[PDB]
Length: 327
Ligand SMILES: *[C@@H]1O[C@H](CO)[C@@H](O)[C@H](O)[C@H]1NC(C)=O
Image 1: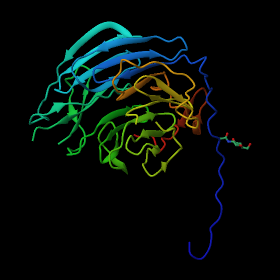
Image 2: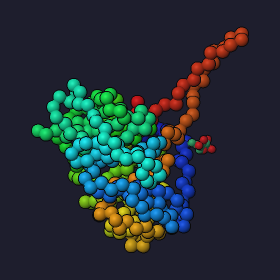
Image 3: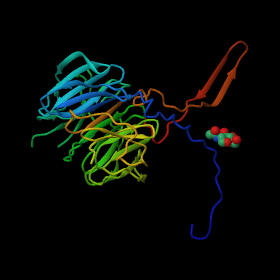
Image 4: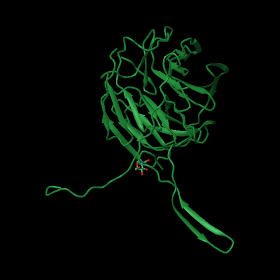
């Protein structure tokens, strides 16, 4: 306060352990880089395959990727949804058209553009476009159990993602990024930047990592939205990205740049050819850490035990939710 200083509150805390660094000789991850017309699967070995997964002549509006089923749903610019299941980077099943009911919620016409996947409830989230407003509305994989969350807004979201484990849906406009839960109870706006680009969500890190192609610098956005932090970036404007540990994937139009966010982009650690792709609006990493079922923190407390002659009623408290987690 103005007059003085209060007492000192002490706390003991340990941060998490260092992630193991895989070199250029021993990189074994797999990626899907997704274009508007050319969707391609690549393996990050020194001897890696540069193979086509799927080619669509129509422009694809948004994608959604599942880990447990390996399915890339496809939504075009018209609004007809094609469900396409793959297996390990190639065709096992073709595209199936999935029809969606409007119901009594969608009173007027609305067309789809957006795709996102919850892996805990197996529940799809899409926002709509009105031919006069942009309104988020949730349904099942089959599609009949449709009900809407939130309120319509005029600003177009360009990218929708799900952090299922912490219970959040992020929609990001050209005006702001927003944070909202799965049941429609609480709605929060995070940060105000004119035209942000692509964001990637890590659920264990609790950090939204975002690249502006207009600014061309790092930006860190937290889940409450009040924390903003830059880092030094290698210079080239990449439309999307993926993060693999301490290494950063930056796709050029002919190669891929492997940097550890301090070395230059002119000398990558390893390069993989991307010559069939025109541009990279969506870089998707195939790790099991991209969709964890593990919340990665747990210790019970307040153990109460009420006993008897030959029995006991024993009650404990669940570990509490964090503010970066949801209800
Ligand atoms: C940090 O160290 C103290 C002192 O040894 C210990 O009691 C505490 O458990 C540590 N904190 C964590 C979160 O491990």
